[PDB]
Length: 296
Ligand SMILES: OC[C@@H]1O[C@@H](OC[C@@H]2O[C@@H](OC[C@@H]3O[C@@H](O)[C@H](O)[C@H]3O)[C@H](O)[C@H]2O)[C@H](O)[C@H]1O
Ligand SMILES: [Ca+2]
Image 1 (tube, protein in one colour):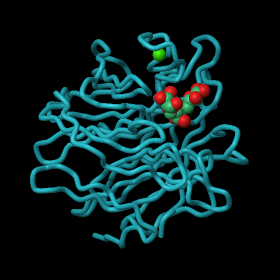
Image 2: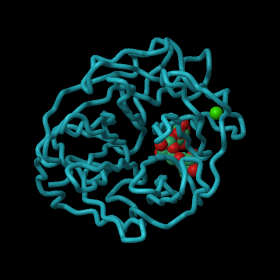
Image 3: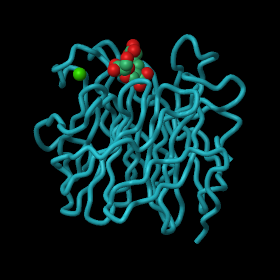
């Protein structure tokens, strides 16, 4: 049943599949109410072999594990490459580079331990100055294309991407502005299914999830419509999409948890995702019941 975790508040889920298990990473909401602001210090890790029963692994990483960060364990994403696990995170940078930043940690296993892979930020606020806000450099998504080129996607208000080196911890080209995403807010997730690329994102505010399709990782991106309605009792809508055991899953968050779930006290949920024959995605139907076990 959704929400899937009832002893903690979890937000901004990311997932990956590794050796027949799905690993789920989420920020932990620790705000005492829904009237002040997000309080997030650490990210939690969970895993499942059936998408229904989840093992808790505990905190895999903390914002303070980056010596150059102030705190704020915001949206993050993990990807496997060459037997390692790279965890791209959003954190508030210390005063040396004011504003939010993207950092990267690395581990030898999906449950870590993880450590700062650079000793400094990968993206700092001052690298991107086409907007005056100091929270535009948040919410990273990393994708490795069929030719072996990795890309870092990110942004709030301004969607952007850049090539990553094969070492996964350095940029390898210019930062590009992404076009084709109407009402872009945040939460980019990129995935590929058959011969189409999909870029889904939080759209407008209060946030829906919209998406665009492209014939290449570079687009051009063609908006296809609404993937998720505004989520129950939350103005932020943050998604991850994965394939597991021949089904597709839409992992997201709501404010439907207890006690007093809400905008700063969120809860991860999961529902199934379905494709149309033309490659478009049916709009999600968010449900109390959630998904049935799907064991291999
Ligand atoms: O006002 C509408 C949209 O809100 C912002 O995006 C959503 C929020 O962005 C992040 O942080 C919220 C802001 O960042 C903090 O530094 C700033 O003080 C908060 O206002 C969260 O992910 C969302 O709540 C866009 O700026 C705007 O279009
Ligand atoms: Ca910036």
